[PDB]
Amino acid sequence: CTTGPCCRQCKLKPAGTTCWKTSLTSHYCTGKSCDCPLYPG
């Protein structure tokens, strides 16, 4: 999911980190005030 700020928008991850990404979902955010794409592609 990488609509925009993800954080809250395209970021439902279990609150990870900024531009982190695990390897299945992708945190790259946390939900709220982020700006990292949680979806490598």
Image (spheres, rainbow, N blue to C red):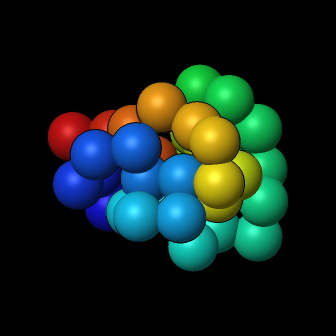
Work out whether residue 16 or residue 40 is closer to the camera in this orientation and state it: 16
* Residue sitting at x 58%, y 37%: 34
Q: Residue furthest top?
A: 19
* Residue sitting at x 39%, y 63%: 10
Work out whether residue 24 or residue 31 is closer to the camera in this orientation and state it: 31
Name the quadrant of the C terminus. top left
Query: Up-down: is 16 above or below 14?
Result: above
* Residue sitting at x 41%, y 64%: 9
Work out whether residue 23 or residue 1 is closer to the camera in this orientation and state it: 1
Residue 18: image quadrant is top right
Left or right: 10 in relation to 15:
left
x, y percent for residue 20: 67, 31
Query: Up-down: is 15 above or below 14?
Result: above
Q: Residue furthest front?
A: 33
* Residue sitting at x 54%, y 53%: 7
Q: Is residue 25 visible?
A: no
Left or right: 10 in relation to 2:
right
x, y percent for residue 22: 66, 47
Left or right: 40 in relation to 29:
left
Q: Is residue 9 visible?
A: yes
